[PDB]
Image: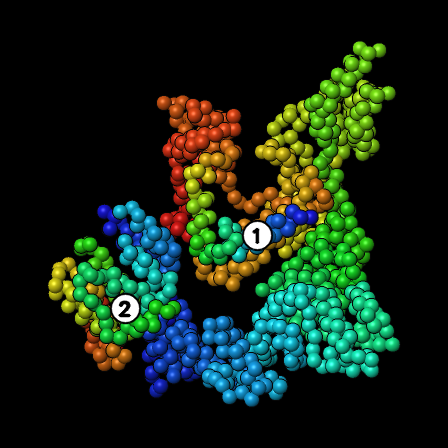
């Protein structure tokens, strides 16, 4: 049952803003900007499966 | 917006009031106050409307223009006004206390807790804010009886007494003033119990009592006795752990007094959570509510013996009541390791089902199919009255389980797992023949599965045994006594039947004809918070993917779908989480023109590896429009699909394993984006708007 | 140009009495070849009183100070030659005392600042003089409006 806890802790860290760095309380704006950059970088958008169709 | 929503109304209101040559003096003041409490946030207009008005709200709104600029003077004014309304005016005292607690959330000056001793210390300091706070907290005696005299908060370590006293005094007299108190009390009792399990705790009066009890012999040993009692009460059959250590050193009469003292040292330690639960129940009775429900559930499951006298007494006796359509997690806690918890959960579920039973749509009928000791009592309790609506849903669940998967194709799917098993068996048989029951009895699991498929298959309900089972009795000709080449017979007798068409699916006249026969049924609410009138129209095999089954209901129109071999339970938890999130936005979903709302997905689990969810509301997929654009481009090129969606990537990735591009996929991505127009969905929503103004809102 | 193809978008977004996020988008979208948008949308974001002094500040140093006598700027925040955006700063005349307040100061400041330049025009002063709060001057000023008054 050590798996559900691994997801609960991840969710608590994402809400606590400790997703990227568990020692820095990233502000809401900083976390949003980081998530947008990571979700919009051509590098990350290129290593995705073909079914995802990141090009479209 | 002030102009010209209120500034244009107050403009003529002032004129209508200036001609005194009826009742145009109270509505004018209300308009001026509403213009003052904005916030956010014209300061000059707020001051002008305050001067104009200068409905007692006009005395509390002025305290907010100061908070916007002068925190100290604003808090002073708010605390001075809070002492004013000693008369029976409840709607203002609670609001003032709430507005002052938020401002008092600092933690910046550090004077409330720093002056905590000033409560009873011959106080003579320091600021008007502290004096007014003390004078208002001392008025609590003039009116959830008590929070903490000396030990509950500071005796064992807790937050500032100021916040607790304010949240408690804000109870006068009736709405949301209990949430701010209960949540705070519980959030701090959690840390108190944590530090207790890590540390310990004891009071002076009970420790002196214990010391004077075990006399004469010695109080030195009484020191360790009280320390161990506190440590145990903090860390917490648990009561027996106290006597375990008490009888170790002393080993001695007083056996009952020891526990009586241990049930008191751990009494004020859990009094925080007790008051939290009391305030939560009071707020539920008077009226986020889901947060309070989850908090109470976690407090009961974590520890129910202390204080059971509150939980067991307030939960069953008018909990909210009820909150069945808020927290369906009560079932997850029904299988608790301790007694006295499920006994109350069963009564709570019975009460929630007695009124608005549609909220619990298949709450236990599905659970009983696969905790059961309580699910059985919950079904009959929630199904005794009006058994028609419960028998109908039971037969519907039975038909849904029958239509799942069906396993008529699962036999071939499970037999196809012999890519190398049958080959290895044939190799071993050939080796044994070269040497010359081991090889014949090597596929015992496959034989067991082929026997189970027939044991479960028996008498288009007549077609499953005349079309799927038409050759099932012969498909095991060689597989039963024994290469094993006679294995594709059943694999194709059912696969070819489905492959004959694209949307291969039968109407309600299928294995579950009751649907087509159920021309009228009571309200069932198939995963919603009332239209299950008679029956849906038809079903489909969903040729898109594998393997749903869409089916309307034509309730008093509502499509759904099945999912065989899929645990639709985590999906239900995620949908509940999304609902809770959306409820968290309702406080801010007020223009808020683009209302914050995460689209839901009504999922109803019908057992392990199953589930009945609504297919979709009106929503066109994005891949649909992408394929439409690809088809349009292909047509324009031909007149000068495929695409395909997957082969299109490999078509432009060849001229670059896994592989390491690396450093090459970022180029194919650009080459694809440079071709696919980025306005496929933009123009889709643009043309799909009947007007240019509706386009903006969309 | 972009300067003219952005003030119209900002004014449109303001007309909706909402969508200040859409204007902050352009404020962060200025990478395509200004800071004026950061305050042009601040009327609905925070308030109309605020975002008014911000526009005045953004009008410098292309001109004079343009500040008014009483603005409470101390605590009021605890809550290139364009030739077009200058007049486009008339949004002040909507965030200015236009919302009930003393408007004469802003009109006088605009006149004094236009005395040093050209192509700067304010709004109708007759429509604003209805703030007399007295039927006498209210009627004396309303009789000059474009519409034809009545006689009871």
Label 1 to label 2: alpha-carbon separation: 47 Å
Residue at 87% over, 76% down = B253
Task: Determine whether C89 is above or below B160 in the image.
Answer: above
Residue at 34% over, 63% down = C43
**Residues packed near mark 2 inside 10 Å, few (<14), some (14 to 19) or many (20 plus):** many
Would you say B643 lies left or right of B526 here?
left
Task: Determine whether B470 is above or below B93 in the image.
Answer: above
Instruction: Provide the residue designation for mark 2.
Output: C96
Which percent across, then down, holds residue B371? Answer: 78, 53
Count of labels shown?
2
Which percent across, then down, holds residue B270? Answer: 69, 71
Which percent across, then down, holds residue B650? Answer: 48, 26
* Nearer to us in this view, C94 or A27: A27
Residue at 66% over, 27% down = B498
* Nearer to us in this view, B139 or B467: B139
Would you say B176 lies left or right of B666 here?
right
Instruction: Provide the residue designation for mark 1.
Output: A11
Secondary structure found at label 2: loop
Q: Closer to the observer: label 1 or label 2?
A: 1
């Amino acid at each position: 049952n050590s798996y559900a806890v691994s997801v609960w802790k991840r969710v608590k860290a994402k809400l606590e803003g400790r997703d990227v760095d568990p020692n820095r309380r990233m502000s809401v704006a900083e976390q949003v900007d980081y998530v947008i950059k990571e979700a919009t970088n051509l590098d990350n958008l290129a290593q995705l499966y073909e079914g995802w169709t990141a090009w479209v | 917006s002030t102009l010209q929503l209120y500034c244009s109304s107050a403009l003529e209101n002032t004129v209508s009031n200036r001609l005194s040559t009826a009742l145009r003096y109270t509505m004018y003041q209300n308009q001026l106050l509403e213009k003052i409490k904005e916030q956010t946030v014209p300061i000059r207009s707020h001051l002008m409307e305050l001067g104009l008005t200068a409905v007692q709200l006009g005395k509390t709104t002025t305290a907010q223009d100061l908070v916007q600029h002068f925190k100290k003077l604003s808090t002073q004014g708010q605390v001075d006004e809070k002492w004013g309304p000693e008369l029976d005016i409840e709607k203002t005292k609670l609001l003032y206390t709430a507005g002052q607690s938020t401002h008092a959330m600092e933690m910046l000056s550090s004077c409330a807790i720093s002056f905590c001793k000033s409560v009873k210390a011959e106080y003579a300091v320091a600021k008007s804010i502290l004096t007014l706070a003390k004078w208002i907290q001392a008025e609590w005696k003039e009116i959830p009886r008590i929070e903490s005299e000396s030990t509950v908060h500071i005796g064992v370590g807790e937050p500032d007494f100021i916040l607790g006293q304010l949240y408690h005094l804000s109870s006068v007299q009736a709405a949301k003033s209990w949430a701010a108190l209960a949540s705070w009390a519980y959030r701090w009792g959690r840390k108190v119990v944590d530090n207790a399990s890590q540390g310990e705790g004891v009071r002076l009066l009970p420790r002196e009592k214990s010391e004077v009890q075990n006399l004469l012999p010695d109080t030195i040993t009484e020191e360790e006795k009280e320390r161990i009692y506190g440590i145990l009460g903090q860390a917490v059959e648990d009561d027996m752990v106290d006597v375990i250590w008490r009888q170790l050193i002393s080993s001695c009469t007083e056996g009952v007094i020891k526990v009586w003292r241990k049930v008191v040292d751990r009494i004020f330690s859990l009094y925080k959570l007790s008051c939290s639960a009391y305030f939560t129940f009071l707020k539920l009775n008077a009226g986020m509510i889901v947060m309070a429900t989850l908090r109470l559930l976690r407090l009961l499951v974590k520890h129910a013996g202390e204080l059971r006298q509150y939980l067991e007494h307030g939960l069953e006796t008018t909990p909210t009541a009820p909150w069945r359509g808020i927290i369906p997690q009560l079932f997850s806690r029904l299988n608790h390791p301790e007694v006295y918890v499920r006994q109350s959960i069963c009564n709570l579920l019975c009460r929630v089902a007695q009124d608005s039973p549609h909220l619990i749509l298949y709450p236990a009928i599905v659970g009983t199919i696969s905790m059961q000791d309580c699910y059985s009592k919950i079904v009959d309790k929630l199904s005794s009255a009006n058994p028609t609506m419960v028998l109908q849903v039971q037969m519907l669940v039975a038909e849904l389980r029958r239509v799942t998967v069906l396993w008529d194709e699962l036999w071939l799917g499970v037999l196809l797992q012999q890519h190398m098993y049958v080959l290895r068996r044939i190799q071993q048989l050939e080796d044994e023949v070269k040497r010359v029951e081991k090889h014949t009895a090597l596929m015992k699991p496959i034989v067991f599965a082929l026997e189970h498929v027939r044991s479960i298959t028996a008498a288009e309900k007549w077609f499953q045994d005349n079309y799927g089972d038409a050759i099932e009795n012969a498909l095991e000709k060689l597989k039963t006594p024994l290469s094993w080449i006679p294995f594709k017979e059943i694999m194709l007798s059912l696969q070819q039947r489905a492959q004959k068409r694209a949307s291969y699916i039968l109407r309600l006249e299928e294995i579950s004809p009751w649907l087509a026969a159920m021309t009228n049924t009571e309200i069932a609410l198939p995963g919603e918070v009332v239209t299950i009138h008679s029956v849906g129209g038809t079903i489909t095999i969903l040729p898109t993917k594998t393997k749903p089954k869409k089916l309307l209901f034509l309730g008093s129109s509502y499509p759904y779908l099945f999912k065989g071999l899929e645990d639709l339970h985590l999906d239900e938890r995620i949908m509940q989480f999304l609902s809770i999130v959306n409820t968290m936005f309702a406080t801010i979903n007020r223009q808020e023109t683009p209302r914050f709302h995460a689209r839901h997905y009504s999922v109803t689990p019908l057992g392990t590896r199953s589930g009945l969810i609504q297919w979709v509301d009106g929503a066109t997929p994005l891949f649909g429009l992408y394929k439409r654009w690809q088809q349009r481009e292909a047509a324009l090129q031909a007149q000068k699909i495929v695409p395909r969606p997957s082969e299109l990537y490999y078509s432009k990735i060849g001229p670059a394993r896994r592989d390491w591009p690396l450093h090459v996929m970022k180029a194919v991505l650009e080459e694809l984006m440079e071709a696919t127009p980025p306005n496929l969905l933009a123009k889709e929503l643009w043309s799909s708007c009947t007007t240019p103004d509706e386009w903006w809102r969309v | 140009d972009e300067g003219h193809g952005n003030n119209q978008l900002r004014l449109v977004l303001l007309l909706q009495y909402l969508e200040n996020l859409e204007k902050l988008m352009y404020n962060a979208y200025e990478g395509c070849a200004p800071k004026v948008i950061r305050t042009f949308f601040y009327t609905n974001r925070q308030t109309c009183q605020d975002w008014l002094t911000r526009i005045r500040l953004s009008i410098m140093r292309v001109g004079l100070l343009a500040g008014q006598p009483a603005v409470t700027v101390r605590h009021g925040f605890d809550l290139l030659e364009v030739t077009i955006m200058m007049v486009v700063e008339a949004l002040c005349e909507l965030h200015c005392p236009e919302a009930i307040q003393g408007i004469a100061v802003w009109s006088s400041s605009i006149v004094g600042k236009n005395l040093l330049w050209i192509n700067s025009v304010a709004q109708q002063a007759e429509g604003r003089f209805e703030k007399a709060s007295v039927e006498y001057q209210e009627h004396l000023c309303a009789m000059t409006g474009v519409d034809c008054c009545i006689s009871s």
